Amino acid sequence: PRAKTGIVRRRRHKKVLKRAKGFWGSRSKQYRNAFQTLLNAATYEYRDRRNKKRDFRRLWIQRINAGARLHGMNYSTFINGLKRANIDLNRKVLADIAAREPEAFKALVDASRNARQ
Amino acid sequence: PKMKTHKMAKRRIKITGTGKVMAFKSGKRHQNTGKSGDEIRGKGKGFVLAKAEWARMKLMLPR
Amino acid sequence: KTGRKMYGQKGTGNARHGDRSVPTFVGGGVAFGPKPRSYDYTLPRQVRQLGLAMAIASRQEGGKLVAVDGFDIADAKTKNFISWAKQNGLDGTEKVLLVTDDENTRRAARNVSWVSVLPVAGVNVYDILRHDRLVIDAAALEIV
Amino acid sequence: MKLHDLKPTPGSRKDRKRVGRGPGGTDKTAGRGHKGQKSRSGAGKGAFFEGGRSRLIARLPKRGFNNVGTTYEVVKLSQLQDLEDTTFDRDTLEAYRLVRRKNRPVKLLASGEISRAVTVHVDAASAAAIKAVEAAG
RNA sequence: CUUGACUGCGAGACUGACACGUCGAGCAGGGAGGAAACUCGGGCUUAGUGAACCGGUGGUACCGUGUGGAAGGGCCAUCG
RNA sequence: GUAGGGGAGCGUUCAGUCCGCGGAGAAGCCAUACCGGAAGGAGUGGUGGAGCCGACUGAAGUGCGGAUGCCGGCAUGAGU
RNA sequence: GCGAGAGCUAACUUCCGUAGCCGAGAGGGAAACAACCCAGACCAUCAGCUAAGGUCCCUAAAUGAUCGCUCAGUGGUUAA
RNA sequence: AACCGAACCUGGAGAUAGCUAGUUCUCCCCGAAAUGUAUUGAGGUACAGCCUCGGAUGUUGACCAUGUCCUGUAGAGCAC
RNA sequence: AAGCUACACCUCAGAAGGUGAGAGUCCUGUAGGCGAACGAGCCCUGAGUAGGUCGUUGUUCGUGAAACGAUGACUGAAUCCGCGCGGACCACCGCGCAAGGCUAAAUACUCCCAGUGACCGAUAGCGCAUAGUACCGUGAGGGAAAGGUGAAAAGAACCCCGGGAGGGGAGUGAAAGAGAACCUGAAACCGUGGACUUACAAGCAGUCAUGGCACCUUAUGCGUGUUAUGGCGUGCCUAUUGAAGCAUGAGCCGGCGACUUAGACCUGACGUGCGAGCUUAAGUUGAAAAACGGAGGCGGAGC
RNA sequence: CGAGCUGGAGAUACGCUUUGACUCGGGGAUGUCCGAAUGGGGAAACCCACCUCGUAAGAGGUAUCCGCAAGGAUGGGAACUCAGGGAACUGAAACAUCUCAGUACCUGAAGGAGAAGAAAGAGAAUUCGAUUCCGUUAGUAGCGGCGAGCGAACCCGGAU
Ligand SMILES: [Ca+2]
Ligand SMILES: [Ca+2]
Ligand SMILES: [Mg+2]
Ligand SMILES: [Mg+2]
Ligand SMILES: [Mg+2]
Ligand SMILES: [Mg+2]
Ligand SMILES: [Mg+2]
Ligand SMILES: [Mg+2]
Ligand SMILES: [Mg+2]
Ligand SMILES: [Mg+2]
Ligand SMILES: [Mg+2]
Ligand SMILES: [Mg+2]
Ligand SMILES: [Mg+2]
Ligand SMILES: [Mg+2]
Ligand SMILES: [Mg+2]
Ligand SMILES: [Mg+2]
Ligand SMILES: [Mg+2]
Ligand SMILES: [Mg+2]
Ligand SMILES: [Mg+2]
Ligand SMILES: [Mg+2]
Ligand SMILES: [Mg+2]
Ligand SMILES: [Mg+2]
Ligand SMILES: [Mg+2]
Ligand SMILES: [Mg+2]
Ligand SMILES: [Mg+2]
Ligand SMILES: [Mg+2]
Ligand SMILES: [Mg+2]
Ligand SMILES: [Mg+2]
Ligand SMILES: [Mg+2]
Ligand SMILES: [Mg+2]
Ligand SMILES: [Mg+2]
Ligand SMILES: [Mg+2]
Ligand SMILES: [Mg+2]
Ligand SMILES: [Mg+2]
Ligand SMILES: [Mg+2]
Ligand SMILES: [Mg+2]
Ligand SMILES: [Mg+2]
Ligand SMILES: [Mg+2]
Ligand SMILES: [Mg+2]
Ligand SMILES: [Mg+2]
Ligand SMILES: [Mg+2]
Ligand SMILES: [Mg+2]
Ligand SMILES: [Mg+2]
Ligand SMILES: [Mg+2]
Ligand SMILES: [Mg+2]
Ligand SMILES: [Mg+2]
Ligand SMILES: [Mg+2]
Ligand SMILES: [Mg+2]
Ligand SMILES: [Mg+2]
Ligand SMILES: [Mg+2]
Ligand SMILES: [Mg+2]
Ligand SMILES: [Mg+2]
Ligand SMILES: [Mg+2]
Ligand SMILES: [Mg+2]
Ligand SMILES: [Mg+2]
Ligand SMILES: [Mg+2]
Ligand SMILES: [Mg+2]
Ligand SMILES: [Mg+2]
Ligand SMILES: [Mg+2]
Ligand SMILES: [Mg+2]
Ligand SMILES: [Mg+2]
Ligand SMILES: [Mg+2]
Ligand SMILES: [Mg+2]
Ligand SMILES: [Mg+2]
Ligand SMILES: [Mg+2]
Ligand SMILES: [Mg+2]
Ligand SMILES: [Mg+2]
Ligand SMILES: [Mg+2]
Ligand SMILES: [Mg+2]
Ligand SMILES: [Mg+2]
Ligand SMILES: [Mg+2]
Ligand SMILES: [Mg+2]
Ligand SMILES: [Mg+2]
Ligand SMILES: [Mg+2]
Ligand SMILES: [Mg+2]
Ligand SMILES: [Mg+2]
Ligand SMILES: [Mg+2]
Ligand SMILES: [Mg+2]
Ligand SMILES: [Mg+2]
Ligand SMILES: [Mg+2]
Ligand SMILES: [Mg+2]
Ligand SMILES: [Mg+2]
Ligand SMILES: [Mg+2]
Ligand SMILES: [Mg+2]
Ligand SMILES: [Mg+2]
Ligand SMILES: [Mg+2]
Ligand SMILES: [Mg+2]
Ligand SMILES: [Mg+2]
Ligand SMILES: [Mg+2]
Ligand SMILES: [Mg+2]
Ligand SMILES: [Mg+2]
Ligand SMILES: [Mg+2]
Ligand SMILES: [Mg+2]
Ligand SMILES: [Mg+2]
Ligand SMILES: [Mg+2]
Ligand SMILES: [Mg+2]
Ligand SMILES: [Mg+2]
Ligand SMILES: [Mg+2]
Ligand SMILES: [Mg+2]
Ligand SMILES: [Mg+2]
Ligand SMILES: [Mg+2]
Ligand SMILES: [Mg+2]
Ligand SMILES: [Mg+2]
Ligand SMILES: [Mg+2]
Ligand SMILES: [Mg+2]
């Protein structure tokens, strides 16, 4: 019994090719560059996911001291003074509190400063 | 098929026993010898160790 | 069926190549193709006699009809074998294997789509196992 | 029984090694190692300096007796067994050779076996228990 | 003064991938020196060396092809 | 986690047995946002116009990105 | 890196010893950078703590507090 | 008879190739070596050494402490 | 209509092929039966020898203790109380009659024919779905690609633009979404139209994040397509101490393309049968099937 | 056999056929020229003759080697058989003996087969009983730079 490759290879190739949407040029049309681009793209997808965690970390922080200094203290002497205010621990995305309710972020500034005295 | 390597047979390598490979003791054949009388005698029958698997298939039918 | 040496070992600028008759060519020569061979091997005797015994045994859950003679077929005509079987629950919702001794009696129905004949000897751990029932008939082989 | 439902004993067939055929295992270089004389093959059980050549003490012939140790011989219950009955009753497979017996633990009751020759100390323990042994005159 | 510059052995260990190499108490046959205990199986020790194959010389009586021998071969010792 | 050893598996053709499907339309092809831990598998629609899926067992010419690999088609250089 | 020979107390030299790394090791730091510093990645999270290394703006985080020092851009290229 | 230190064709013939290149489905578990000897040996092999699988045994393994013996480097010294 | 359905029927015949799609009962056939004038076919018993020396050689026979047969050169016997051999050679003991011829069957092969296939099905299979052609060579010699309207030609009268080629209609046909560049018709490649986009931009071509604009058939969502902008980001393989490497390979896509087979062979793991015992080989007979066959092989005694 | 037929051929005209076509089975008879080629020559398929037949047109003969003579041979065959010749790459991890292997190849002869064949044998039982083939003996006995490696037979079981 002979068992030629037919239908198998086209199906595999077409699944690779379909992963290529708006890939530029022969990235979208030739199988070999499509598959090769996907190897490097693997690298990027995994690394980036882990990194995106750390990137939103950064955006968080960068808003929080901007509001903090608007109230006359930096990030450092703030997220300290909430933690030194101990039970105050809300921590996760204080960014949004600073970015939408300033009546609240002002009270948190007063709390941190009271804790540092 | 499968030959025995007849270089194994009347040469040292008795196959015999609990499956282990005896061989002889070698130096001072009939090449010249002054040398000691307690070595000229201690050349009777040795038995090798970590090569046996090679020796066996030289002669697995025990010729 | 092809030739020679093809051209320049070095210097043509084309790839290396040697003759037109190799598997890397789309010409000819399968590398590791089928060649004629035999697959038959002497299976040990104890196991095939145990096999047919187990096969007959497997039909004692629900199956295996009479080993004896039961031939009221008008010399040899299928419609009358169909009637004989139809009185035994062999209406042919189930394929059935028959074994016997009289050419006159198996000849009755070599045709019918359910049954197939085999003479005494020439039984088959596969045949009796692949039909849905066994009309053992021929009592001689059945008893010793 | 259902041929659909036949099933070989688990563990009685294992699959072949498909060497090549992926980076899911056994990639590129096959089972093989990389370079070296491992490639389209040859050369046997030979080290290609000096293969442990030890000297050769030699004598060509041999011819050995067929064995009947008498430890089975005593539980035998049947006694006075001439040995041409024995090859054609059990034991002593060899047609090309001659038969011999030998001491194995006990002897016990009487018997009389006509073997081609036997150990002298069988006569030390077959003659006791009132038994003859016929070397083939 | 004389040969222990011995025959049959080798419990145990050092050392080496092997194959080789090293040391050896003690047992037998027979010696040697000593009054004895005892020490002798080469040299204070560590270099002075070659596997295997094929053959020469001396013993032994194992093999020896129908049998009885012999040719030839094996074993022990040695030489190249 | 590289050579390497081990484990469990996906898909292709052929064969045996079963369950079936098909001109009110089969394989193949085409699109797709569903499913499975992966190999993959289904749903629906478009095309096609005569065969074919699923399950269990068996046997393999059984899985390609490379080989200045082969055959074929088509591009770049260029309206040069 | 440490301990040595060879070398010119040369070399991203060569040859041994020794530990660790790369080899097969992703992640953070060292501008970039196999080997150096921190640390060994089963999968997911728009949650929290630290290591090396950092906190003027590129660029996450003290234009931090207290004593001094250097007015050379020393910092940000050797010596007699 | 458009490539002559030995023509062309067909055959042995799938010459041989310790040398180059290539060797394709999937997830899971473990995970090396570039050392030592020998080699008409040095980019090749054989045996060790390091990996894995299965069986047996069953803490015999690992660091660390205490006890004990072995050593002639660092340093130092001038008694050879 | 052969499929579905409902009622029947044959079967020594339900093997198969054809027939507008899948037919036991429509055709050809099948089981079975018949079947030709000429037709093919089961006192003797071997001499230039036997034997020998020189060179050699064949069988396991490589000058080895090397017999025996074999001839190239030179020699050269004996008769039935005789002749050859039994692996230097001798005696004994055995086997056999050389130098004359013929001889069926069991064996091999496959140009040719039949049947069959866990054989191919258009880059496979023979080189050829036919061709030793075309084509290449002075020659010997080498050597291609090869396919498909439709059930049936009913193979497109007539009209329209065009010298034609080509097309558009009308017809036929189930279909012309089959029209003779005639089954399906992938991909690379070339175009036309549309959505979203792009003319201060530095770029292994992605990836992740967020805004914009479209869209709504596994689909109003943790959607789909496409964008702008930020962060991050050194092709793939091979070969390597070390590859984005200015080191190898590769224009692209399609298809072809590499760990196999064999043998009573060795050695292990797993599984089955029978177990102190297990098993057959060649073959014989039966084959829509397998039984028989102990010759022989492995354990069982070692040194 | 019992109505079609007129090759593939698909294109018409022309016919033929139930006093049997066409097709199938079996015989006859024609059979240009070359080709073993063979009357002589030759660059195959073309040139040139002679002798009897003899009315012509046409027919028949004319090579060599075997044999008195009949009658035979010459050439051609995919592979298979036997014979006369007889390699080398290769393996031996180099190479001389050795292997590859009496393999490939060339040549001769023959057939449906061929070869071989009726014991001055095998062989160690005073067993056997022409040859060939298969199984096993057995990789045993042996051969061998005693290296690489090569490798019987008898007994026994079968085909005949
Ligand atoms: Ca222009
Ligand atoms: Ca230009
Ligand atoms: Mg990234
Ligand atoms: Mg935080
Ligand atoms: Mg022995
Ligand atoms: Mg090029
Ligand atoms: Mg072919
Ligand atoms: Mg197999
Ligand atoms: Mg296998
Ligand atoms: Mg694996
Ligand atoms: Mg490689
Ligand atoms: Mg090769
Ligand atoms: Mg070999
Ligand atoms: Mg050497
Ligand atoms: Mg036995
Ligand atoms: Mg004294
Ligand atoms: Mg002593
Ligand atoms: Mg001698
Ligand atoms: Mg003798
Ligand atoms: Mg002698
Ligand atoms: Mg449909
Ligand atoms: Mg799909
Ligand atoms: Mg149709
Ligand atoms: Mg293949
Ligand atoms: Mg690859
Ligand atoms: Mg390619
Ligand atoms: Mg091309
Ligand atoms: Mg120096
Ligand atoms: Mg260096
Ligand atoms: Mg490496
Ligand atoms: Mg590491
Ligand atoms: Mg790193
Ligand atoms: Mg880094
Ligand atoms: Mg960085
Ligand atoms: Mg730097
Ligand atoms: Mg560096
Ligand atoms: Mg790295
Ligand atoms: Mg923190
Ligand atoms: Mg710190
Ligand atoms: Mg900042
Ligand atoms: Mg400051
Ligand atoms: Mg020229
Ligand atoms: Mg030319
Ligand atoms: Mg040349
Ligand atoms: Mg080649
Ligand atoms: Mg060859
Ligand atoms: Mg060579
Ligand atoms: Mg691990
Ligand atoms: Mg050494
Ligand atoms: Mg090396
Ligand atoms: Mg090893
Ligand atoms: Mg283990
Ligand atoms: Mg221990
Ligand atoms: Mg411990
Ligand atoms: Mg010092
Ligand atoms: Mg039909
Ligand atoms: Mg019907
Ligand atoms: Mg005569
Ligand atoms: Mg002669
Ligand atoms: Mg001679
Ligand atoms: Mg010789
Ligand atoms: Mg003689
Ligand atoms: Mg002779
Ligand atoms: Mg003799
Ligand atoms: Mg097929
Ligand atoms: Mg073809
Ligand atoms: Mg084609
Ligand atoms: Mg051809
Ligand atoms: Mg020409
Ligand atoms: Mg021509
Ligand atoms: Mg057609
Ligand atoms: Mg046209
Ligand atoms: Mg027209
Ligand atoms: Mg119509
Ligand atoms: Mg159209
Ligand atoms: Mg169409
Ligand atoms: Mg046209
Ligand atoms: Mg069709
Ligand atoms: Mg088409
Ligand atoms: Mg356009
Ligand atoms: Mg456009
Ligand atoms: Mg500008
Ligand atoms: Mg702009
Ligand atoms: Mg630009
Ligand atoms: Mg972007
Ligand atoms: Mg390099
Ligand atoms: Mg690099
Ligand atoms: Mg480049
Ligand atoms: Mg490159
Ligand atoms: Mg290179
Ligand atoms: Mg290039
Ligand atoms: Mg066997
Ligand atoms: Mg054989
Ligand atoms: Mg007719
Ligand atoms: Mg016609
Ligand atoms: Mg002529
Ligand atoms: Mg002629
Ligand atoms: Mg003539
Ligand atoms: Mg040569
Ligand atoms: Mg060689
Ligand atoms: Mg030679
Ligand atoms: Mg041949
Ligand atoms: Mg010939
Ligand atoms: Mg001939
Ligand atoms: Mg016989």
Image (cartoon, coloured by chain):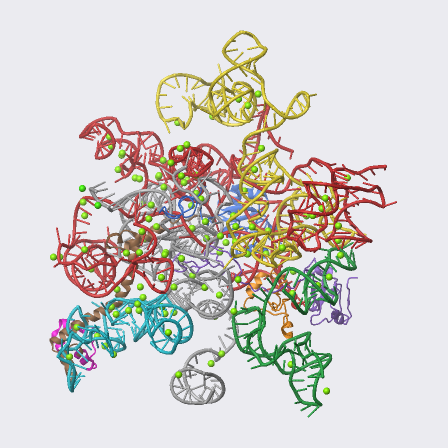
Chain colours: A brown, B orange, C blue, D purple, E green, G cyan, I red, J yellow
Residue C116 lies, in percent from the top left, at 52, 46
Residue I142 lies, in percent from the top left, at 43, 39
Residues in magenta, as a range: A77-106
Q: Which one is in front, I11 or I85?
A: I85
Position of the C terminus of chain A, as image quadrant, is: bottom left
In the displayed structure image, the side of residue E20 where residue A74 appears, left or right: left
In the displayed structure image, the side of residue J78 where residue E24 appears, left or right: right
Can the viewer see residue C117?
yes
Q: Is residue B44 above or below residue J63?
A: below
Image region (quadrant) for ligand 17:
bottom right
Q: Is residue A99 above or below residue A15?
A: below
Residue B47 lies, in percent from the top left, at 59, 69
**In the image, residue A82 lies in the stretch drawn in magenta:** yes
> Quarter of the image holding residue E45?
bottom right
Residue E48 lies, in percent from the top left, at 58, 72
**In the image, residue B6 lies in the stretch drawn in magenta:** no
Q: Which one is in front, I278 or A76?
A: A76
- The residue under the point 64% across, 75% down is B38
- Report the predominant secondary structure element of the magenta stretch: helix
- The residue under the point 28% across, 60% down is A41
Q: Which one is in front, I267 or J118?
A: J118
